[PDB]
Amino acid sequence: CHWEGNKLVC
Image: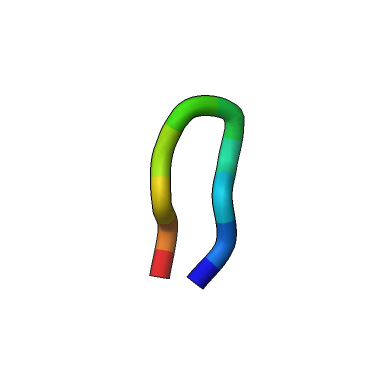
């Protein structure tokens, strides 16, 4: 999981 701009992507 990574943090993109304003949210969590997994």
